Length: 410
RNA sequence: CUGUACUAUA
Image (cartoon, rainbow, N blue to C red):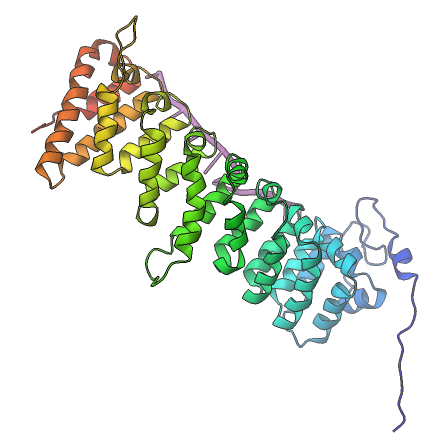
């Protein structure tokens, strides 16, 4: 028949008429309320589409809960499609609803029901200002649900927008860190290798690693790059881990004594396996020659404690020899390192661990190692006995004496 | 006389 070109009707009054609300706090339009901030029972999704009020419901708590509850999950439903198109016609409106205290929860809902086609236009909108969406307290939850839910090439294309950005700022941010960890915990290393190249710099690693939030970023990266373990005929992850663990090893002395970085150092020491070489470097270059000072610190004494727990015998021997005979006695008190750590409110925990390691190590298969652990336990016992009159009045001394109890130091 | 962090939105 004859062609019919149906243009859409111009309506530049919708926003001006949906800007009228009852409460100045709510944004729900007055045609849809019941007077009490709730959504009237005659209101249907066809009414929302007809009055062009998707934004105004999404910016209100009860209107957005209405949208989330009645949003059709099926991708071929007509109302689903019309609502999705209203969401994504304007990029700036979409990025406003992502950054909205309430609207984000709707955006996450359309992610949960999405198909590759929808994910493509969602990804293209998010990529234009991904970094600022990651800093936002509301939009970062959208970004993380995207990283989980998108097809892997789409999420890769998204996370690559973070390259050449101020990643120190984003990593130590209250909101941004959980994005970066999500990337590292979900996407293939090929999608975030620029993070490992960024943390290869010493300055960036220290600033990010010595932070409330960035130390969890560094630890999540180390966990993901090391958990590969075997299943690898080649490497790649080993070279990336090596590139990162290099800076940790070069700056471990500072990191081990920091209020936050101590936990990353403990993870490296405690992990073993693929991190077991790096563990050894940390003890030989940072802990050794500094056991007495680090065992007196609030943060580093946990590092010394896990180092006694997890080290191989050949390093336990050097640590024991440093405590027992590696320090000059105090000029006025003639006090050695062991005497200091017995009565010290942090170092007592180190002494309790030395005893535990020597007790567990008596059951080792090698005879000489068993005799050496027995020798070290006997040295600690003698000093505890010469100071038991004072140690029995402390909780720590009661723990120490009960640990040395009824032993066979063969 | 007992000693450290993050685990964030209605």
